[PDB]
Image (cartoon, rainbow over all chains, first blue to last red; front, side, top):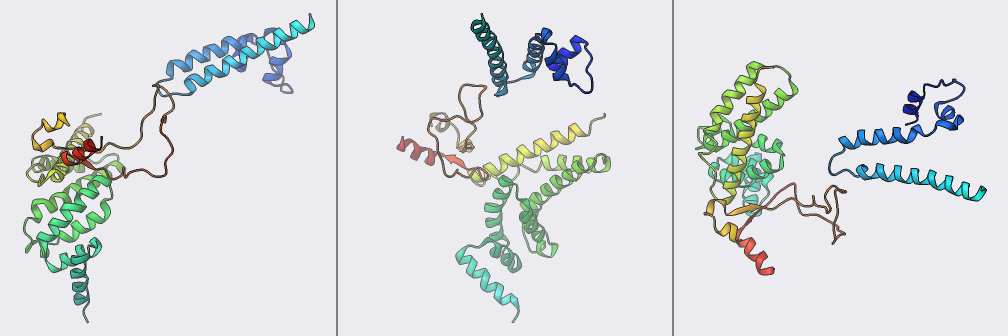
Length: 81
Length: 155
Length: 62
């Protein structure tokens, strides 16, 4: 998702920096990663067939991650209001 | 003393006690073909065809196939070299599998399978166990026939 | 039992099925059981055929 968002963002990466480093530097546009994840999600789930545990595991992972960012943003906002 | 006598000892002792590794060899040497039938066919044929351990079995069928034996044997052709040719067919198919292009061997296999498809069912079913043997034999020969017909198709 | 004692004697036997290969809630992990734990398995490399008398004894048990 990081590299896909980098492609969609067409921002250069210095060799001293890395892809994740550049993405994490300009925090203004990190939102691209969620829909990149989602696109990869349907791409994989089209292929996923029956008798697949990753079929649910991937969704579990993404659910936890997104809930966690919403969680941390909410708590920081509430604490620092 | 010739081991002839010793292996007669082992032959009767196994006739009484049941050690296949010895009855097979020694009865074959002693020209006991009907008994070798009612042992190998009854037990080992089914065992090996079910369990895919055909090495020892092919050894015994080869030693059975001896024409010096065969001239005194009756109906070795009827079942024995029958199973033996099935072994030849599957093994040279595996040869074909390790190969990529051999038409002058695919045609041999095709002639062999056409010949065997009409000789599979004449025997077997001495019992329900014979029925099982015949069923597996016919199913495998049909599978091999469809395989060879599919592989002998133009690209 | 009924299905088979219907039949003529040629089909009078059935192979014993192979052990395992069951789970619940389709699309799940390959192994699921309610009565678990084991220390050995019946021979599945060598299969067996099940006949009227065998089936009669199993029914008698049941």
